[PDB]
Image 1 (cartoon, rainbow over the protein chains, first blue to last red):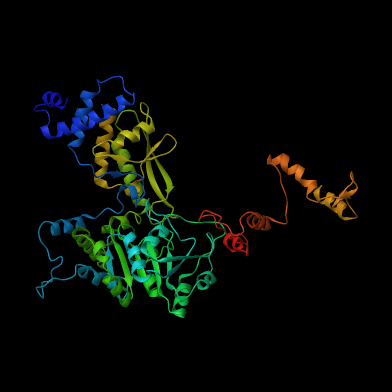
Image 2: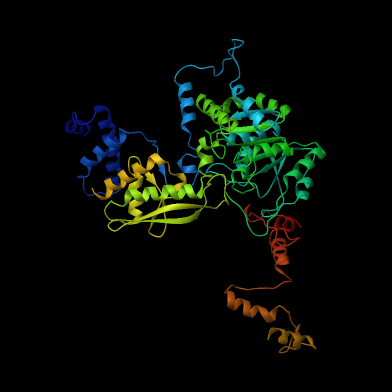
Length: 443
Length: 90
């Protein structure tokens, strides 16, 4: 019973956790024994103690990312420069002029603090910001095309993440969905073909987390705009990457689309996540024509999507950085634009820390990985891994224990050889890497 | 080898639509199908001009006016005028 387990650990662990550890372990042996899968009760003493050790720590923990994927959906997307985290810390520490204008001394709209930055950086007439890009979509449809049709290419009906899908959202959006062209190809005649009285919207979505090769055709963006200005229809581009600037300017050569460029091209509305290529905290970012934004703003779901104090502040600081050309300060930009050189530099500095540890086979390989996970699907870039192999322990079991470390470490596996992509690894992590390994193979 | 076998059948008359046994017309599809049933292992078989029309046939035979469910990822445009949605319509 739970009272005997409270007697076994008196001062050992606080009474509150011990009973929550006996209640979860006791439902686990009640169901394992009912199903007839357990013949021994002896593991009960150690496991109620491991639960207590575990239940006494946070579920969400910082993790050292070895995979060399900058934008790791599973690992928390764009991490944040300390500068920013500090400004977020300060604003959360007490009250703040969130919804308060200091000039007039009367309430004010919280989305007003930021928008000045967006409209300067992109060039759009006005702007706005909601919970994530997801809702930013759901908002631009339900606002603009409730009960009327929207035209989109059959190749752009994406499923990104686990629950999101343009057709399943747009439906619930209340917009009527008109799918032109074919999977692989879509000409301009396909869009123009389906125009009619009901058509309220010309939407294009960017294939963020996939890509098609082979015989493939797509509708030029200059073309969608010409088309809409013909029949008097608004265009709506879901970047999704929400890349904020031209990326070629950093030496990486891709066609990824960005706010500034897409707007000056003549699209009427653009959106994208903030926790992607922008580098910030999670946010739906929407920019374009004044008359449209106003309309979005006034829709009463906007209040159900409006951003929290934490992501609001933190977004301002990241926007600040971007105005100050302080690029290297926003993690997701530095990690992609890191010099091939620089990577090696780090690679061998690590190797140097592990030489001494027993049983460790350590080598430095130059590999081609694909860094972007949720925003740059075709991108392939050279990065140096430190592959390691232990005589006593196998690569699989290695990863596993590394994931259970404090802090935990997550990495790629490849042909029974553990790898460490240096693209995503922070310096202060190296010392913690060495201490982790030596605690595992010497214990 | 092929081209010769073709050349030869083309240089004169042939039992194309003619069954020699019964001395009566026969289906031209009949010559081939025996090979197809053996190689594939299906119950029966048939042949038409090209795959394009083979799709068109199987839809219009089996689904005229009824629903055909297909993956949104599989609606292709192969070649310049063949498109599964465009033909499936017709």
